[PDB]
Amino acid sequence: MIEEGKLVIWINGDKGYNGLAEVGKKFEKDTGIKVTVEHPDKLEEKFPQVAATGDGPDIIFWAHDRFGGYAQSGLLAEITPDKAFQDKLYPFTWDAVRYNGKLIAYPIAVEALSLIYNKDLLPNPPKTWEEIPALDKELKAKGKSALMFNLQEPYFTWPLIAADGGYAFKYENGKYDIKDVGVDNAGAKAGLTFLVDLIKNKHMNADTDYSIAEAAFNKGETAMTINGPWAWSNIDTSKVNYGVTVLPTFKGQPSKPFVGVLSAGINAASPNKELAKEFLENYLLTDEGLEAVNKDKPLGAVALKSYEEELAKDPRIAATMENAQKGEIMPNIPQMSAFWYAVRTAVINAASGRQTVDEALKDAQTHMEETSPAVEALENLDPDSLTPRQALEWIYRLKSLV
Amino acid sequence: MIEEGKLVIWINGDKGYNGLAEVGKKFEKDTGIKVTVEHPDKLEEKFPQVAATGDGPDIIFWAHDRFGGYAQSGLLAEITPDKAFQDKLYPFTWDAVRYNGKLIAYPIAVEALSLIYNKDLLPNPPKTWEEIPALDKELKAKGKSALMFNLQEPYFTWPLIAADGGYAFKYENGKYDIKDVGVDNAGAKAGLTFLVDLIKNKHMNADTDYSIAEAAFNKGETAMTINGPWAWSNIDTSKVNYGVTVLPTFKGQPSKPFVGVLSAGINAASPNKELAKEFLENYLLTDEGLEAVNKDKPLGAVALKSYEEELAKDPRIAATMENAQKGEIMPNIPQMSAFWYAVRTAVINAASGRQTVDEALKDAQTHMEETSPAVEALENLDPDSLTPRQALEWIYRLKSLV
Amino acid sequence: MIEEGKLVIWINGDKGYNGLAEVGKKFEKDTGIKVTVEHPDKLEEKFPQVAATGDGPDIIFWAHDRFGGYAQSGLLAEITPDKAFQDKLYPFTWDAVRYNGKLIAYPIAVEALSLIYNKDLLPNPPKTWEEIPALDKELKAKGKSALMFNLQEPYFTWPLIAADGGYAFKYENGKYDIKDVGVDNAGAKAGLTFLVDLIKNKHMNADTDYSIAEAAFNKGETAMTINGPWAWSNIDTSKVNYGVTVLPTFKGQPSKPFVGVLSAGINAASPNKELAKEFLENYLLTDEGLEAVNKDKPLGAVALKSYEEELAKDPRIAATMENAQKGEIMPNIPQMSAFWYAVRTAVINAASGRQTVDEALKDAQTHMEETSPAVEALENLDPDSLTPRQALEWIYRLKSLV
Amino acid sequence: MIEEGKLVIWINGDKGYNGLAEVGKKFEKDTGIKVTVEHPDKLEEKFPQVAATGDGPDIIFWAHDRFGGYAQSGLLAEITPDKAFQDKLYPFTWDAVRYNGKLIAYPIAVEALSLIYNKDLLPNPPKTWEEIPALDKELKAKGKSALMFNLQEPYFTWPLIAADGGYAFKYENGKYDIKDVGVDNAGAKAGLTFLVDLIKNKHMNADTDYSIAEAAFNKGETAMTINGPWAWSNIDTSKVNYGVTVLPTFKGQPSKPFVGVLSAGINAASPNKELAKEFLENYLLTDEGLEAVNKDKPLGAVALKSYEEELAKDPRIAATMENAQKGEIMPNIPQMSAFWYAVRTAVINAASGRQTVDEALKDAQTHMEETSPAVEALENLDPDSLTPRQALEWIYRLKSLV
Ligand SMILES: OC[C@H]1O[C@H](O[C@H]2[C@H](O)[C@@H](O)[C@@H](O)O[C@@H]2CO)[C@H](O)[C@@H](O)[C@@H]1O
Ligand SMILES: OC[C@H]1O[C@H](O[C@H]2[C@H](O)[C@@H](O)[C@@H](O)O[C@@H]2CO)[C@H](O)[C@@H](O)[C@@H]1O
Ligand SMILES: OC[C@H]1O[C@H](O[C@H]2[C@H](O)[C@@H](O)[C@@H](O)O[C@@H]2CO)[C@H](O)[C@@H](O)[C@@H]1O
Ligand SMILES: OC[C@H]1O[C@H](O[C@H]2[C@H](O)[C@@H](O)[C@@H](O)O[C@@H]2CO)[C@H](O)[C@@H](O)[C@@H]1O
């Protein structure tokens, strides 16, 4: 519904979208404007697909890394908070949503992965990845496991892969050298080899995903998981006595998570840009709107200073920020898209044994060094959801990309 | 689509297509099968576009260099001539139409560019590229120019670009290394600089194309042109007293044109491939059949031994084969269209001043380094000719190439 | 396009097109001219779309009501049969194909809908629409329904809509007043309310279409259907013991179907109009030629006198002509497609509950009041099938209609 | 150039576009952002044509009557002046640019037509239209004429046509009855008949246009003209001693000009919406920016109160506002488009004698009563400037309009 007079909002299924709908319901009450909160699959790839043809939602929620590609494709309206409102949010969150000198999204919350452990099974969890094998051997004799976490999304494995020196793009003086990529280097090989060794040695399963790992931790079947603050409420529900701590170190060096700022952008094709701004600034980015959402699924360390002053006292948030400090804020450059695509394939191929670690990371590097809109776009395009008219605009749009 | 019981043939506009239809009419009269000869513009692009879908002609004529890409795209039937027929043609012409061990077309005639000169204006044509400036200077007084030829198609400029060392792809053993490209080497630079200098120094105009150069020569306005046998008949209609001879040398080395073998491929989707086979084998590739086309526009050095014995007595044909010998048969690899794209841009951009020679030839190199099945097919389609449903099929077809 | 020396024919999918091709094969054997019989979906729309451009078949078969619009768009050749041939067909069938004094098609057969009933389930079929509810009530016990017929095409619902006074356009003198429309009068309302009430009261389902109603009858699941002669052969294959009879009365008045004359028009752009003329005149419109089609699917009451003398002995044909007499030959004016559009929406919207009967029939009226050449052609094209260049031609073609 | 990083501005050729470019030059100097001011032909019909396909300028200048159609077609961004800036402009100018509760453009200036007369030829010009014949008879004996004004644009004749009761749409309580149109009524017939009588009697020429009338007044060939403030600077240049006064009355009732507010909207497809706003609010709508433009071609009675306080003392401005008071502020409803289209045709057809006054105004009414996007759009479409891709989006856009 690219309907004027309405707001349509997209956000990932793991965030507090019932919470957000409650904020929509306060906006409809005060204003009469209906808000529909939807959480469709793969929405970070659908958005650029349908916004290109002037469709999609008024408001898109995602971590900030995808937004520079959006802004570059002219898919986002420039947001114009006054100084009084900008002063409400931590300066480094605004930096994460600035692209080519324009603010292209409102920052909502800072996310980092942490080690979450069952204190009943494991009151003193391991400081190192290298201890996990022996600890799994121990828990196996009891029909349990040391560690389960989503191995389907490179976001979850990247902190291990980066530990010993893997990187996406080289950061120098204020700028990413997109010709300097480090997914194929010795440090990235070391961390992926360690992961694959865990599966080879039957300490993890290659096919473990988000939901398999959540159920296992939440039922008492595995001692540890890796996950971000959004996950904590399902763990409360399970009554498991859990702690949130620093990720284990690897080769005597910290795991270095990629730090994401959940952000909200306004589709540049939206006929509702003023309503979107009123909803975001006046309803969502308040102690009340952030609480509604956070009480649903935890946001992390929110962008809003007044509300953050409270949540910062939560030792789980302390631990999140501790982990964020060891990792790095994601780049928002357009190539992040190619980075994730490449690494996802490499991790799955290495984990399942279809490829060696060496073969996998060298194709991931080759894929990144071969990134260019026209083959790349074809790679992110889902034609099963293109109408003939959308496919034609896309054939032009791709002739011109070029 | 394409209907059974009839043949549709496509052949380029500069070829003897009325001659060709004379052969078709003999065929319908003997056979009861109607032959429709068509000469659509940009056919070497239109072909891959419509044959992809199982439409297009039964028979396609073009120089052999496009046929590798068409065969790789599954568009051509492997042809099936017996040994006795194969014995009738020259083995080198069969090599030009062999792709991964398969015969993908019937060769027709060998085409090389020669220097064509007006014997009244210039009875002793230039041995070297280097003397042409002074000659143009001298012709100016008479209201004439030294030389005009098509600068819009890199085919006509290649011979000079290659003379001092430019090459498409390195040929070491039996193979073409697609990684080792020679459009940007010292010889390619020196050849193109000499062309640009001809333009800078007002001896040629960047804008000159096929029809412009042809009019000027045939109207006795320019002393020389560079063209292939198909042009001789318009010259003859013109009564210009012309000769055909070896291209001039550059830095003391022959001009090296890229030699094409005009070939007929059978569309893989054609229901008439036996009919195609009988027409081509028993009608076209005969003394009688080839004479009818060559009498419309000359074909060059024909592939069929018995007829070439005749043609080869003609000094314009010895001139053609001299140039052919000095140049190189074109590769037929999929990557040739990428080559020709890249070089077409370089020549037009350098001739126009839009780029230096070094800038233009670097960009030609980079482009060839970044080719792939997907983008080559893309260089091939214009969206202006695709329906939305077709575009949607193209998005899938494109995806399957990535 | 369209090639000389051959015929391409389009005929609707529910007709005897294999029979028709049998006539074509006799024609090729006598004539040496190949006949290609095609039955594309939505042909009565696809025809105006491709014939506008001078493409499409040589011959088009449809009921006469579409032929006024096709002739007005300059798409049909005026046919040229001599008096002796014209004497062979019935004068009323020639009137159906006359437009502004010109013969625009050869009539083939008269089509009217009848009540078809299962003689085992219902040996005495209902005289009146009004009794069908109680009959359905009684059939329910047996696991059967009273009546199922296509509710998606207003052709099948019109007979009841017209019974009590609905009409398309008023016919006073010799002419149809396009200003005086009768889709929204008291009789049209009463007829449609009775259909909607059948649905409200669970005696029919809004969703029922051609193939659904056909399966149900032919599988012995429903006692009655409403359909034309073309359906009888599937019923026969079915061994259902069926009869064909007069439609039931409504408010004491005959059902009045809109009677079509299945006709063949010659495409104005066809290069084979003498061949079309010889096939139609001397092959199709013969005892032998019509028997071959009618043996595939029955044609109805054929236009050719000598063959109808035979067919008319068949009680299913007397039933057809009874219904034909009680209903009205369709006008052939350009405005008939607008009529059918308008009523198709009304019936579907009323049957679905989306609109009351009064709302739906008012909107049908308004629509017909607002028709024009431009928007009628628009109801005809789908952009999904137009290339951009074609679309541009359509914008001009459309402008020339305003 | 839908280039981000640039502003492209469209404004009519009769406004001070050299002036406006000087404001662009101050914006480029202070900001580095290039501004291109263009004045293309028929820009009020091109804008909706090219903005529909995401092309056109960042900023469009036109009188406010066209903007409600634009806003309705989703072609305009909502503008969001703060209260401090809105307070700078007269409240009634903001009303003129509000559509469906959104401000859709910045108001610049109020325009009304006045009677401009040569005080040397005619020190006491006529209070009535009915005096013009005798006064022309008098000036003719001297090789001069009473009155010449653009008869090609209904804007110039509408005040006479409305005098005795012609109207576009009936205005009641706060709303236009679009079903109540008055171009065919007795008052509109009376004023058009008077115009046509002037031409019949050789007092005016049907073909006199803007430029013919300007030259004539400006050279001393005609005593009077009708025109808005933009025209006054060319009259200064001519040194003609002119006055600006109330339009003559007709049938003892005032001429009732349609009053236009020159406005500036921001294309909703612009990637430069923030720059556009900075330029409009901060550079143009200042005493300095308005003066730059006004010193070029007079704007009328500007929207900006501080600058208006000065120009209001100009007796020419007093006379403009006197005339505005007798006429009416144009509606901005989407149907204004159809209104002008209809009346333009009627005036030209009546003036040239191809149609009687009665025939002309009744077709204009019939055209208005038949207004609907799909025939209407086809009427405003210029396909000579559509690319194939633009034409396809338009065939969809029009299928959907609907
Ligand atoms: O795995 C690649 C993927 O990782 C990140 O996505 C995170 C997201 O940021 C979190 O909020 C949560 O949803 O987990 C996701 C991983 O499943 C990047 O944000 C995303 O762009 C990237 O593709
Ligand atoms: O200019 C690039 C072009 O060169 C060759 O085309 C020749 C063709 O072989 C000749 O038969 C003649 O028609 O002139 C053409 C150039 O105008 C290659 O065969 C072709 O693939 C390539 O694009
Ligand atoms: O439903 C509207 C439709 O009715 C008629 O079409 C009939 C056709 O005449 C018969 O031959 C048979 O095939 O069924 C069709 C309906 O499914 C009109 O002839 C047609 O123009 C109209 O749109
Ligand atoms: O004539 C119909 C036309 O009139 C008005 O246009 C005016 C414009 O407002 C003035 O600023 C000046 O340019 O003269 C124009 C008439 O030529 C309406 O503004 C316009 O929409 C309408 O079509």
Image: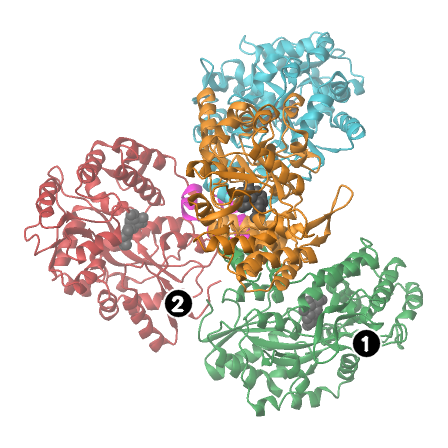
Chain colours: A cyan, B red, C green, D orange
Q: Mark 1 to mark 2: distance in Å?
A: 51 Å
Q: Nearer the viewer, residue D232 or A296?
A: D232
Looking at the rendered structure, which numbered label has been put on residue C241? 1
Dominant secondary structure (helix, strand or loop) of the stretch shown in magenta: helix
Whether residue C28 is visible here, answered yes or no, is no
Residue A111 in the image: state x and y as whole percent: 64, 17
* Residue type of the residue flagged with mark 2: Leu
Query: Residue C369 versus residue C273: which sits nearer the camera?
Result: C369
How packed is label 1: few (under 14 Cα within 10 Å), some, or many (20 or more)? Answer: some
Ligand 4: give its quadrant: top right
Answer whether residue C296 is visible to the viewer in this image. Answer: yes
Question: Which chain is home to disc 1?
Answer: C
Label 2 chain ID: B
**B357 sits left or right of D329 in the view:** left
Q: Position of residue D201 (x, y in %)?
A: 53, 61
> In the displayed structure, would residue C269 be above or below residue A264?
below
**Element marked by disc 2:** strand
Would residue B200 be found to the left or right of residue C60 on screen?
A: left
Highlighted magenta segment, given as a residue range: B374-401
